[PDB]
Image (cartoon, rainbow over the protein chains, first blue to last red):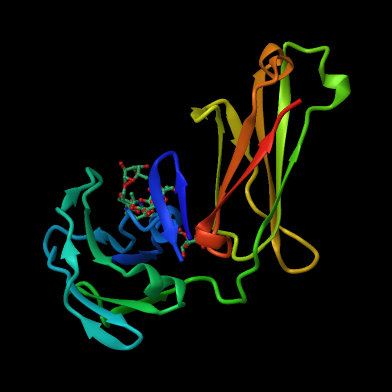
Length: 13
Length: 207
Ligand SMILES: *[C@@H]1O[C@H](CO[C@H]2O[C@@H](C)[C@@H](O)[C@@H](O)[C@@H]2O)[C@@H](O[C@@H]2O[C@H](CO)[C@@H](O[C@@H]3O[C@H](CO[C@H]4O[C@H](CO)[C@@H](O)[C@H](O)[C@@H]4O[C@@H]4O[C@H](CO)[C@@H](O)[C@H](O)[C@H]4NC(C)=O)[C@@H](O)[C@H](O[C@H]4O[C@H](CO)[C@@H](O)[C@H](O)[C@@H]4O)[C@@H]3O)[C@H](O)[C@H]2NC(C)=O)[C@H](O)[C@H]1NC(C)=O
């Protein structure tokens, strides 16, 4: 699905 | 005459979908008598025209610094497309052509392991939290630490080292006051890499 780091949208599958 | 240097985008701008990756074509040693610089950009041999020229910068060493920037797509760079910058200037006998792209080779997923501080270190004021990131390709990566959702600044990360199997590994060392580790706070190693699912992974670490 999606990954988030410190609130920044990283990437999504 | 003038020289040309073509740079890749920041690895963070390519893996984080919120950011914008750009390839940078820097021309140095531009003369004052012929400061005009023609730029031709090619993506996989096809010329593109959406590049912007940065403001000319006097270098106070008798030369100008002229820079062109081409925004790239995230998947375009990650799929290994080649970007050619052709620089033309009246001080050049022939145009200079530079071409860059992502490091070729099959991307390999990094394995992220958190190593607690050694029992022999608990006699010091500050203990060392270790994050091992190995088996990744290409070398482009970014490593950060955080605790209870708050970033941790006091850390150092070694440059990537080529391993015997053709992949890269590195270590990140977070330094914390021993009390914090003995308190029991969870610490997280945050690694960003193209071969990770959604370009991101976290590994926790606590007593
Ligand atoms: C007139 O003055 C020009 C600029 O001068 C001002 O320069 C600075 C450095 C002060 O010291 C002072 O002199 C002046 O106030 C001179 O231009 C410079 O020319 C040299 C070569 O002639 C360039 O060196 C190359 O540097 C590449 C890396 O450059 C990155 O890192 C530099 C610091 O290490 C940085 O200054 C650069 O701007 C550049 O930064 C990168 O930019 C991209 C995109 O903008 C960004 O994404 C990056 O994050 C950013 N990086 C960093 C760390 O910030 C090398 O890759 C390159 O190397 C290869 O080729 C060499 C030759 O083939 C070879 O020898 C090497 O081993 C290697 O294989 C090379 O070393 C220098 O970058 C450039 N400076 C700038 C600011 O552009 C000019 O030379 C001078 N003229 C005369 C006649 O004196």
